[PDB]
Image (cartoon, rainbow, N blue to C red; front, side, top):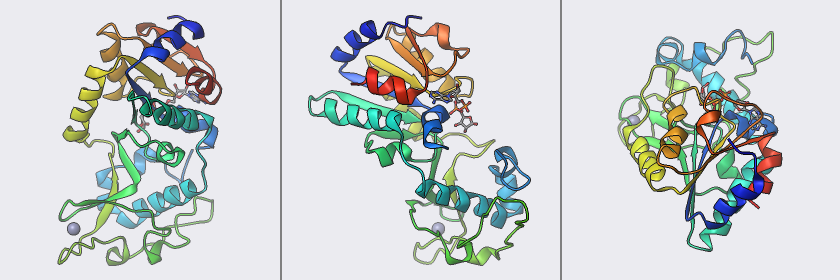
Length: 260
Ligand SMILES: Nc1ncnc2c1ncn2[C@@H]1O[C@H](COP(=O)(O)OP(=O)(O)OC[C@H]2O[C@@H](O)[C@H](O)[C@@H]2O)[C@@H](O)[C@H]1O
Ligand SMILES: [Zn+2]
């Protein structure tokens, strides 16, 4: 895999359709552990939610509230500025993210496929309706709840006071619209993804470990068509040798240059 910025820029100057796949590394420079005695694998499951809907909500309230505090970094801003600039030229730029933090959106990204959901979306467990939700707090019973520090315990909010569906006559319990461990990704989103990968002529893979499916396989799918894929990561990954470029470093340094 090459590290030639100049050779990358030749492709970038001419690309009609850029796909940018992002993961958690893209938000590292925005300052985005354990929450109380648990890690994500113990909370972000349907079984956890079924057993303690209040505790899973405290956890999601806390993450939503922390986000309000976080700012997109130079990486997220370079990606958003790119889309705005090319779009004045009829050139397409889309972001396919694994992240649920919505910092791409806060940076000004408009073409965004969020394959794992969003902290800022809800789904009704009764009627299935999805909606956006930016309210701090999401419900008054969660106000001040979710503190991760030692000495905090379960709020034990009765389920009828947790977020509820406003559809007429529904009244159901809402959950975060995020893909939990064990759950399938939405088939409709994956078709939109397949369409973007098939049609792109330059692909960037940014801050992802490239080992978690199905996103692990997106950039290799593109590189297999003979399209250049550029990886932007602090380290090599197991997929690195499948790609045309590798640009090592924090993406807040390397992206503003590559996408200038
Ligand atoms: N500043 C940075 N710039 C670029 N890359 C970085 C930076 N900091 C870390 N990275 C890289 O980001 C990657 C982070 O990998 P993961 O934490 O595995 O995140 P991601 O690939 O998004 O995980 C996939 C999925 O796994 C689940 O845990 C979660 O649902 C996530 O969506 C690593 O390859 C790491 O080198
Ligand atoms: Zn409902």
